[PDB]
Amino acid sequence: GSHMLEDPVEGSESTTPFNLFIGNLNPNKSVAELKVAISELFAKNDLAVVDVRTGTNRKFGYVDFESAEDLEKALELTGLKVFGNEIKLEKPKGRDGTRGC
Image (cartoon, rainbow, N blue to C red; front, side, top):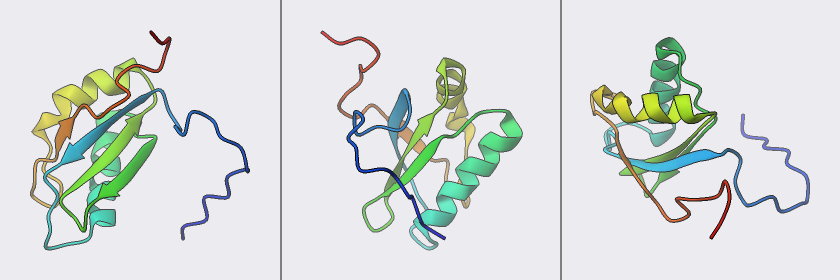
């Protein structure tokens, strides 16, 4: 069901290199279902969704990718429609993370 089972250790508080924020989620259904719709659409698109968290009761969720190729296809993935709602993306804080300033 939902047993992350993570070890007691801080690791950049991140699970993947490519991460961002998304919005436009069908508020008439569940945000968890909207995630699977994006994980299934990316599974048939040949993407690689590594993480997908929900945002607010059900207005927007975040998602992490597994490469620059999953992030570049994620950009062209604006043609989505989770539960009939083209999920939108966004650049949250922490844009960098591969090197540092």
